[PDB]
Amino acid sequence: PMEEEEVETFAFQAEIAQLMSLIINTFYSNKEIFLRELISNSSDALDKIRYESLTDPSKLDSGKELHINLIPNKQDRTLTIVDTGIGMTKADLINNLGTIAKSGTKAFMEALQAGADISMIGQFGVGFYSAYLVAEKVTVITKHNDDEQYAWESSAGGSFTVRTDTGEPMGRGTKVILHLKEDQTEYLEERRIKEIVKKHSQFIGYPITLFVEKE
Ligand SMILES: Cc1ccc2cc1-c1cc(nc(N)n1)Sc1cccc(c1)OCCCCO2
């Protein structure tokens, strides 16, 4: 029988929308840094659950392994980054993925306008948005302890959606699914992914596994 699901559509905060339009509509040469930014957010989320587990060990009931998985899919042109970190509550999601102003937004846009390399984004606290250098649409699935699994999605254009996820349960953590632009398929290649992780994400304190679909 027909199922019904509630959806909430939100507008991005003005400067976040302006930043996303700048990232999408301007040429940048060193786009590979998007992966460093997402792995760095996963590493931070893994530290959060690790430290919380020291006080309340039952916070690991949802999965004891602390790690990052990278899953390129050449059939549907997606690159997925999964972690078993702390995950996001509904408030963490709506607050960190678009509704709240970030102190570094205006400074970062002015710095990009002056010729700064896109690699500077992380320093400004808006590193996630680098996903739009390579992706036309980003889906974020997240699961925090004592809360439901949520799905966030945006193709930019000024809006994002949030819904309770009725899909595949994750025990705990965050999955970022990058629906790559047609000209950015190099980020589905095993060699290219290894190259960029070696260059930019070599001091990550958690194991990372790259899953490669048999050719
Ligand atoms: C997908 C995402 C986008 C933006 C972002 C964090 C994550 C983001 C968030 C998380 N995990 C992953 N992998 N990415 S868990 C989390 C939960 C609450 C607060 C968190 C992180 O960080 C607060 C600092 C700002 C983080 O900004």
Image (spheres, grey):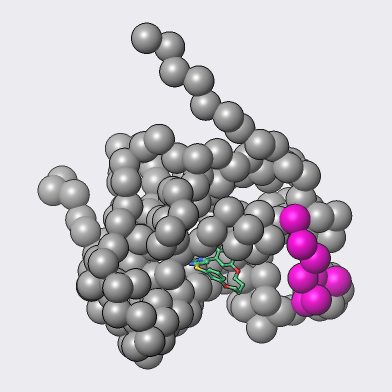
Whether 105 is among the magenta residues is yes
Q: Which of 92 and 184 is in front in this view?
A: 92
Main SS, magenta region, reads loop
Residue 199 vs 152, above or below: the answer is below
Q: Is residue 194 left or right of residue 21?
A: left
Decide if residue 123 is in sight here.
yes
Q: Nearer the viewer, residue 149 or 20?
A: 149
Query: x%, y% of residue 41?
Result: 50, 73
Ligand 1's quadrant: bottom right
Classify residue 48 by image quadrant.
Answer: bottom left
Q: Please provide the residue range marked out in magenta.
A: 99-106
Decide if residue 67 is in sight here.
no
Q: Which of 21 and 185 is in front in this view?
A: 21
Query: x%, y% of residue 77?
Result: 39, 42
**Residue positioned 60% across, 62% down in the render:** 92
**Residue positioned 85% across, 55% down in the render:** 14
Residue 167 vs 124, above or below: the answer is above
Query: x%, y% of residue 214?
Result: 13, 48
- Count the numbered circles shown: 0
Residue 46 vs 77, above or below: the answer is below
Q: Is residue 29 left or right of residue 19?
A: left
Whether 133 is among the magenta residues is no
**Residue positioned 67% across, 70% down in the render:** 126
**Residue positioned 32% across, 46% down in the render:** 169
Residue ranking furthest to the left: 214
Q: Which of 25 and 129 is in front in this view?
A: 129
Q: Is residue 179 left or right of residue 107?
A: left
Quadrant where the N terminus lies?
Answer: top left
